[PDB]
Length: 515
Image 1 (cartoon, helix red, strand yellow):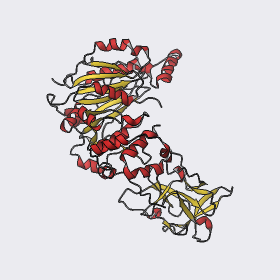
Image 2 (tube, rainbow, N blue to C red):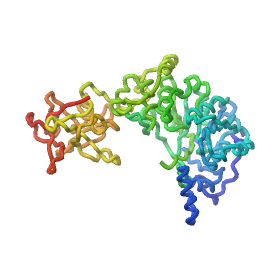
Image 3 (cartoon, helix red, strand yellow):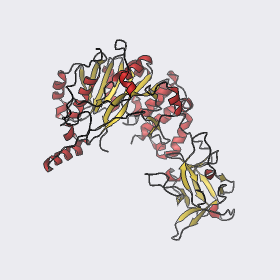
Image 4 (cartoon, rainbow, N blue to C red):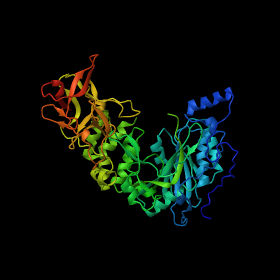
């Protein structure tokens, strides 16, 4: 049986705390409550509880049925080097990760586990961790000589790795049964596929393992270049033959991934010129795809990650500047602070991009992320909209963030900072409030105030009540209601807007775009 791991989990014990990844709850006196709280304050994870859960626990395999009956040829699958960087990790979570890899990964495929101590200061992480792992076949420890950060610590591990495939995990995870084979099987058929497990949540307080039971969410971004999840689009569903095939992901949705070692080297690994820590995966994502390149999530590979109890805008700007061509303006327009960031010397990245003969960001949007609406931002038809009548006041939409279409459109003092005063007038005659998501200005049926609704998807009908005529006189006309957009003052003298019978005179109805 070539599936056998180097070490076998002891038999599952349904009485043991957290067995199978079920939630754990301790009955604690007040002293013990205080110990629990203090470790949470220090680690942002319930280490008190982790310490009372086995380092070897089972996780119930709730994958789609087809996953569980897949057969692998273990003689021809590539090997891997699993790479785990850490900094001041609690003992029980770090070790549970190590044992999980050892106990769920077939020995014929697991060449090594390489742990990278990124200048930890905890004394238990010094010579005792070396002693503990000296008994664990194939586990290697490297220590950095300065504080490197996740990316560079990973790269240091990668330089030591000699497996066919680099598999990057992190230092508080637990692997599901059969997590590894699907990543290596896919890479064995296409060495340019960067393949990620589905990352399941392990609850930081209860240690419950929340397994995604069906189709996973996949990775994209919004035009602020903030990571956002999205559901798998129809095109990609129809491309795939089986619902357990890999799923193309426009961007990476976590830090866990497997890549051919040689291919990672060929792409230049991570962007070393970054200096700042965080957000490096957007740059990696664009480079993988543009330089030919697949980034996929594998529904049969599941790894749980302990998301702890709760900015890198320079690295986001760096990704935009290297990869996005003309489309970076749509980003800057909607995240103006990004214009100020020191993204750094990108000369060598521009050279890399040419050596690799990478394709354009236009290609990327059309072929990798066609479900993303791309704004036009036509010259003179985007920015803040200023009143003539109350000429200190700009159109301003300000919702409560627990439902973006909760407010009504209004006025507020022009700031030139975008955000709630950024608007786009569209070739399809929509007034879009699309700094964050694609929201479209509407006049509801028979009302006189102006709301927002989700814009139509590309190619779909433009509803009558979100059509706007923006005449060359500052008149913003709304055909469905027949009324015009007018600045006014409420009872209390607060500037505001309303739909009133059209009056080319009444200056509160004349308006102007600004950049």
